[PDB]
Structure formats: structure tokens, C-alpha cells
Length: 156
Length: 156
Ligand SMILES: CN(C)CCCN1c2ccccc2Sc2ccc(Cl)cc21
Ligand SMILES: CN(C)CCCN1c2ccccc2Sc2ccc(Cl)cc21
Image (cartoon, rainbow over all chains, first blue to last red; front, side, top):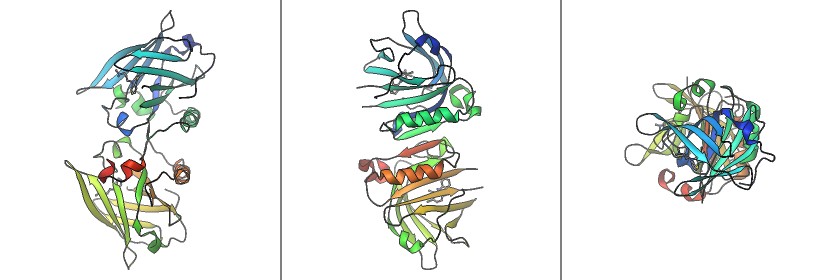
């Protein structure tokens, strides 16, 4: 991924978000409701020391679970790192802070991204920017959700 | 759907095709490998009387089945009709006859479409046209396949 935001004021991205759209390099990453990249954002929490913490929802066994994950900071302001079996990088491509924010999760050759929004509505404008950002990238599946699904656990 | 091809010479669309990309109004139509719209095109056969016949592949129980379906002709050259529990319309939006062909299956509020190609390669140009044609339409999932998957039963 070759697109980060400059002057990333991480403190300003805290609060409430909606995973409006999702996309992945491989069909099986967003494939079924249980698929590995199919993860729903509830909340972004930065820590005082500048780490970034996710609140998420996942369909796991027979239902919608809750989760926390903490992405530790780096030298480049917009790149974070999560400790799993892999080297998992999170990158903030772009955000205007108060409507939308775009980001990608990547490893290593797998890659997923998302268009986050503040309210339960279809920001047409946000979807463009998200589309522009991806045509640089080798994606093979995309999803987006309606306002009705946006107010449910795990998106219905 | 508000886009058909004019002067549709149905005889010229016979032979071999590859379901390069797919898209649907609802996530669950292309969702899992078993999903209702997830149907792979092997061959288009017109009949002498101008009916249009599909050869397809579907993942059904534990494997990739074969199928035939016959879409009967109408007054408008580019619209066909299949007899199921529903009124199922097929529409040919566009084809240059020798590289790509776009079409949509619709009922009634469900809708899926596809970009068909002649060989196992990514026609970048074909994907544009397909993208143009859909932004008129309320889609919420898209897929595309690589050349490797294109030579397998049911796309791997
Ligand atoms: C335990 N899980 C639910 C979380 C890892 C899922 N997840 C993910 C998915 C597909 C490919 C790469 C990644 S890294 C990542 C980075 C940030 C976030 Cl928010 C999610 C992910
Ligand atoms: C028995 N099945 C495998 C065939 C029906 C599936 N199929 C379909 C899917 C989702 C929504 C509407 C339709 S009508 C249709 C028209 C032409 C073709 Cl080629 C396929 C379909």
C-alpha cells in the first residue's frame, strides 16, 4: 500500500464509526459472514502514549462477539502494528476527521481495506475516494451496507 | 435495468465464455460459493428459432455440478425469459461479440450481472464498461477472478 495521510492527528479520529464498505485481495477474506476480514468497527480509541485501539464485532460461533485490539505506534505517524503470529500493519490512507476515514490491514500476501463513516447513511462522496484509493490495488471482492443494516449487531 | 444493446445479433454470441466478474443487489446472492447468483458460464447456445441456452456450473452439495437453462425469446431482441416460480428476465446490455458481453438476471427485487470474456485473461477494458453500466444500479457486492481460477471447475 502506497497511500498514507500526512499530518495525522490521531487524537481527532476517536469516537464512533460505521464500517460502510469493505474490500479484500482475496474473495475468502470477506467471503462468508465468518470470513477473516469481515470485522465490524464500533469505536476508535487512541491511548495517551499514541497507541490506537479498535473496538470491533465478529460473527464467530453462533453469534456476534465483541473484541478489542491494540495497534502499537511507529516512526511514521499513520502506520501501526499488531502483535499476532504475523507482522500485521494498519495504515490510515485518508480522513477528514468528521465524516469518513479510510484504512487498510495488511501482512507478510493478504490485504483488506474499509471506508468508515460517522453516521448510518450512504456518503456517496466517501465511496469515490475509497474507490480511487483501491484502483491502485489488486482487489477481488467488495461489499457495502445500507443504513438499516448499519444499526444492527454484525450488520444483520 | 435501463440498458440494452441495439441490433443484437444473437447468432454471433454463441460459443465459449468466461465469467470474469459478477455483481448483485444483495450480498447473499454472491455471498458463499453456494449462493443463488454464484453461477459460472461455460457456453452460450442460441437455437434456430432464436431462443438462448446457457451452459453453467454450480456448487450444489459437495461439488461442482453442470446445468442447462433455456431463456425463451421476446419482442425486444435483447430481453429473454426463463420459466421458474418467478418471472426471470435476462438482459444483454452490451457485447462486441468477440471479446466481452455484459448481462443481468432480474426478477419481480433481486438483480445480478456479469462481465463475460472469451479467454482466461483480465480484460481491463471490459471491466470499465461493466463498471459504467452498474453505477446506474443499486449493487452491494462485486467479485472478479484471476486467470488461474478461470481454468478450474467452479473457479477453484
Ligand atoms: C481478531 N481479529 C478479529 C482482528 C484481526 C482481523 N484483521 C485482519 C483481517 C484480515 C487481514 C488482516 C488483518 S490485520 C487487522 C488489523 C486491524 C483490524 Cl481492526 C483487523 C485486522
Ligand atoms: C438454476 N440456476 C442455477 C439458474 C438460475 C440462476 N440465475 C439467477 C440468479 C440470481 C438471480 C436471478 C437469476 S435468473 C437467471 C437467469 C439466467 C441465468 Cl444464466 C442464471 C439465473
